[PDB]
Figure (tube, chains in turn cyan, orange, green, yellow):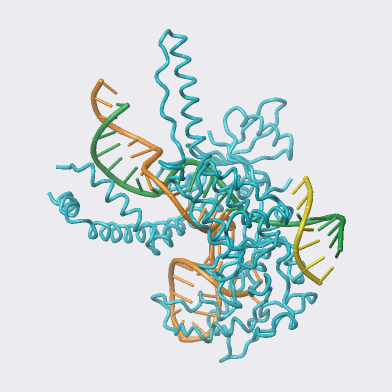
Length: 498
RNA sequence: CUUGCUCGGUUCGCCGAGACUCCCCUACGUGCUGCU
DNA sequence: GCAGCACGTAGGGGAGAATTGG
DNA sequence: CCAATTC
């Protein structure tokens, strides 16, 4: 059974007024502010919000949070049930910590009593509620508008909101296609491919980029062009695919080419689908993020063919391998070593079902290609270039009492195990606030995923088995392991860690 | 494979290659060594 | 058990849709 | 047509 729904993001094109001023957002902020700052005793009292119209009305009357015009049950049940589950998520953290600690006590003290040693005194189990009655780790406010069935995405029509400048396609007509005869464009027009790079044009299944894409005009050292933004923006808007969400009076318009690319690169839909089918591949409950301008869609349970399993290991590993050999009688295991010169070392195998046990059939070994290593080396140079900058910036801003000590640390004795916390926390804060650090932390994940996909592809060629298994053992080692472990969660392939 | 993101090439006309599980908020922790 | 390194980690909460009632 | 119930 399919039980994983990956995301897909689209861009907002037009708004009635900023997303933060919507009554849905204001009521969400009010409810979140009231529930979080109320003691444990009164949570039970104000915890009868109910899943009905009468219950919601009484909850708002007994409390004092401004209903702000918003009075829709579908949406208030999401604003409330989320807010109380977050409140019962700071209690649950301390509860699980104290449960692990009490289980440690139940083991150790009972073992000591069996050895004649009396149990030690019980610890002061931590409380999530501070001095008077309030949560110490107060949950923050979540800026997000969680859509529902009544406000689900619909294709645009001229008799929806006439103020929209750009046109809207027919919801029933088949969707357009990008320029298919790219070699038929005359010279001097957009999209012209000059007559010297025509031979070495890729014959693969590349994704097609239109000439006005930001990737073809971004400022990079080799690009001697102009990044005039207005022309590209209007050229893009002239060919958007508008879908629209209306909540009461306000409305927001999305460009749906993101969903098109999402269904195109995964292969769930071929060219020639309508907009109704395109929205069918996604849920009618998107999530809006007012800070960026994104709208995140998730696929329906059934669109993708991933089971989203867990990395089973140990005793269950042999049972899993026996079950898979009971399936298609050709399974290719791949074994990953890491920590040996290049980041990835792999070892192919094939396993059969010889009655009860397995019969491994070695197939060889593979080393990462050279271009991938070059990309990784360039990434390492970039990361070590930003690190020596952000760490220096963190050191500079230190208080003079700590600044002098840290300066001495660079000078030439190792001491002050009390400013280490200071430099650690401020380096963490700068890392969280450094956008270049965010990009160079996303590049690590992208490159690790490139490596993992390479190994997974080449373990289907050497073994010629559609079904595969992955073995890993418990720098790039951490990110590589994290990327490899995600395969069970993301793509369904087992990860038999041993 | 029409938007968005990342890396490279250029004759600057755009083309070769990638990822697609993502969001909020909160604490300060996780590994690796050295001695008991 | 308790220091010194380095480097981000851990763990709460999210992410719909059939029906039926005026 | 569009909210409100319900699992």
